Length: 479
Length: 120
Ligand SMILES: Nc1ncnc2c1ncn2[C@@H]1O[C@H](COP(=O)(O)OP(=O)(O)O)[C@@H](O)[C@H]1O
Image 1: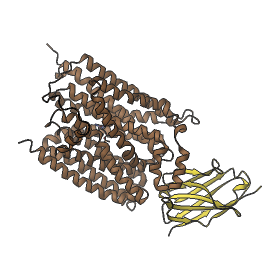
Image 2: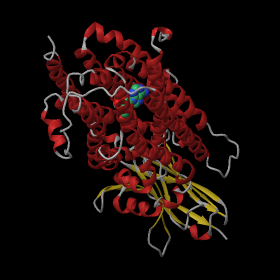
Image 3: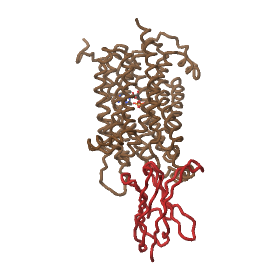
Image 4: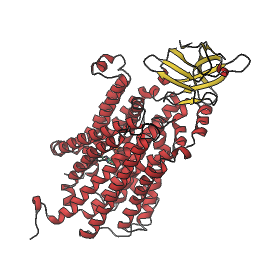
């Protein structure tokens, strides 16, 4: 006589409710972290948004590869329960320590004098690459905030999700997980903006962004502990299926040719192609957008309030479009839904670049909407990222996870951990490498925006050419 | 076609204030690395202040805290606000747009300078 509250069994409810509530808390922290990490490195003194091309390739990329190897080594020395804590607790300690301890000490540990000497000896083109050494502690926060979205959002959660959840519940409640975790963006974006509004209490003296950063990093710990408490509960009071595997345990002792196995497949060879094409294109657009952001919001608090507003808008757009996807998929197909994201990103990016390039003459409409050309660029790039990233979260990520179904059950576990951890940073680092070569070749990033559009078309025209290759092979493992 | 014209220099008492103006033509000042130099008769040209396209400001130790370099994008002008002027600040101040990589100077455009004199 098991009850079926809301038509859903009360035994599965004890498994799904704390799981979507966890993914709510996980994306609540990431919304604070991924917003603060941009406020931290872009609006610092002596740094610009041109640090981002160099942050992602030389700092964020090898630390993601370094974490992959450490997490893979940690997977075969700790239990599944212990592996979750030993990955997520150091994140909680770091962000809590950064708010309360490491950020106030930044003025003591940041070599602002040695970097200003490098800036003169090496010139204006190198403000970006030198800025990594100025605010290296803020650059470490950047990679840790980047690793939260790649490990906690993707590896830690979905690894625990796909373990306790059956295939039938994963087809019914996973779409609800994204819906409830975009309410997290709406609420954490309001949280980022609320705690970014300068108190104006004690206008002189105490840093306004310091009290802002301490309040938010306190929530990151509190909402991060909620992830650990929601994890302790499902593992103690919810029956774990321990579903029987089909393969032997003999696949082991692989640390270097696991990558060779993962690249031998012409299937993962196109999954990774899509996961890099997105990330290359998104970087190519968003680094320029964030340069416009720094030009428009120079103080950390203005930038953080705008990032909170932008996070709320991203949450609402992604909620709407995750509601629309569950009709787009059924009506059209995987191949059309895999075309929507590259096309929307390409069109939004070319519209943004054709406003940075060919909008100066078309200033009449910019003034008509009561804006400056820079504010118009800021809002157009904000819409670019909102549309592209909501499109991702609602069709590309569903298309990605709807392609791992016809595989082995051990290739997928360490394959879409690999794909995430070293293909999202890999794609964004490829885009960042393009942008940083163009920075060191043409001086500023503003001189490089005509060539950003040509490269954007090349990556997208292969993004579609690789989705069709995966489509013609996602269709051929079906009737 | 790049030109820099300086203005605002003049006589002030010790401890007074001035605002040197740099009207630039042929390039946007927000995309440029702008600097203020000063040269007094009998001494070599001395770098005073610098502003970057990112808005980052750098100052010499002798003027740090008293001088402030900024720019107006709409006017395409670079300003040097000189407060608490000492008699040792008397020099011809040059505004300069510049670009270089390590020691290869891609372009280097100067102004004709403006005289700043601090009385005693
Ligand atoms: N608001 C969101 N809704 C759903 N998924 C999200 C959201 N934010 C981030 N994610 C997921 O977190 C994972 C890591 O995020 P990230 O690396 O930041 O990618 P991106 O910057 O493209 O959003 C991505 O798969 C992304 O889809």
